[PDB]
Image (cartoon, rainbow, N blue to C red):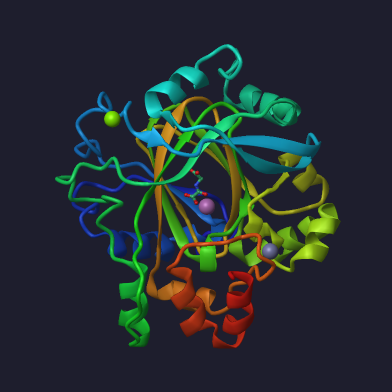
Amino acid sequence: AQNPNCNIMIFHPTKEEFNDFDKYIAYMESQGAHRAGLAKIIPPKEWKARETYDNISEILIATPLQQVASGRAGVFTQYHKKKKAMTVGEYRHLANSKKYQTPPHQNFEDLERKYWKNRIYNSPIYGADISGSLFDENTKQWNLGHLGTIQDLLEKECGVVIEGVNTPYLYFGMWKTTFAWHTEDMDLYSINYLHLGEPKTWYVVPPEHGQRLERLARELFPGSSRGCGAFLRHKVALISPTVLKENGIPFNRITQEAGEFMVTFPYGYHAGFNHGFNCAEAINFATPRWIDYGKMASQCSCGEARVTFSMDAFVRILQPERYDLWKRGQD
Ligand SMILES: O=C(O)CNC(=O)C(=O)O
Ligand SMILES: [Mg+2]
Ligand code: NI
Ligand SMILES: [Zn+2]
């Protein structure tokens, strides 16, 4: 069995190996990469996403979100308070202001210590889930707006044509902006490209151990768990590495830098934080191996998680028994 300890693997494809996305994903899996839940892919030195980032300041962040924490330093939830629209140029200046800027630090480990010690005491502002792309249309390899759609994958594997579309999203971050513990919708893959700026630290639990995380989360968030059998789908719960180690949960950590891709694998729980002002682009995707995970994915039917149009068909075709309950939660 490849990668039996479930370590995060890092890949350095050549330009020729970067031509066929599906083939390279399947290659990474042949080496055991999925067992970690997360892999890093460093593009060939010949490749670029676009020419420059000099012309992005006029992108609008229609609904910036202030991430307000409740709890204790290592175990907290966050809610998202809506703020007035601002441009990416305005958001960059905010991120670099004395109130929000990254503090002085020694290295990535010291910054991680500071994050876990102090996150709860501040409320950073996050631009999330903005439909769009920063890949040049003439970038032909690993262009996250030109991938095969998940609807076409389900049709190729199972024969059923379905409605829906699959497009990328932009994320504008600052110091302390946080992504809560979650798997992807319908336990899909994701791919994330860090276009510019400061790093992103990731934490991940191996798919084979995901239920261990879920059991800890039910213990640590007992009211949320009573509310919804799939409450991690609400994307609000944070648990620190120290707390995970105290409870014997298997996990790994890695820091993504500008110019690097990360891939999350089906049913790989992940969480993390941004080091400072940055811009990432991400999209969900599928492969033949995902279908069996999609059929088994939990679902939120309580009303909180509220998702994309395109999840309807995936539930309808892969989970017909759950469809009626799930849909009542969406209305
Ligand atoms: O960059 C982010 O906002 C965090 N992204 C993801 O959870 C992802 O790509 O799965
Ligand atoms: Mg612009
Ligand atoms: Ni994710
Ligand atoms: Zn729910």
Between 101 and 241, which is closer to the camera in this rendering?
A: 101
In the rendered image, residue 81, in percent from the top left (x then y), is placed at 63, 38
Instruction: Work out whether residue 9 or residue 50 is closer to the camera in this orientation and state it.
Output: 50
- 86 sits to left or right of 73: left
Indicate whether 70 appears above or below 94.
below
Left or right of residue 269, residue 291 in this image: left
Q: Residue at x 62, y 76 (%)?
A: 328
Q: Is residue 219 visible?
A: yes
Residue 65 drawn above or below residue 205:
above
Q: Quadrant of residue 82?
A: top right
Q: Residue at x 58, y 59 (%)?
A: 183
127 in relation to 164, above or below: above
Quarter of the figure with the C terminus = bottom right
Number of numbered discs on residues:
0
Say which quarter of the image contains residue 274. top right
> Residue at the location (84% across, 57% down)?
223
Residue 265 image offset from top left, x and y in percent? 49, 60
Front-lying residue, 315 or 19: 315
Give the answer, above or below, for where 297 lies relative to 176: below
- Rendered image quadrant of residue 182: bottom right
Give left or right: position of 290 versus 166.
right
Residue 275 at x, y percent in the picture: 54, 27
* 17 sits left or right of 205 in the view: left
Do we see residue 1 in this rendering? no
Q: Position of residue 25 (x, y in %)?
A: 36, 61
Image point (47%, 58%), residue name: 33
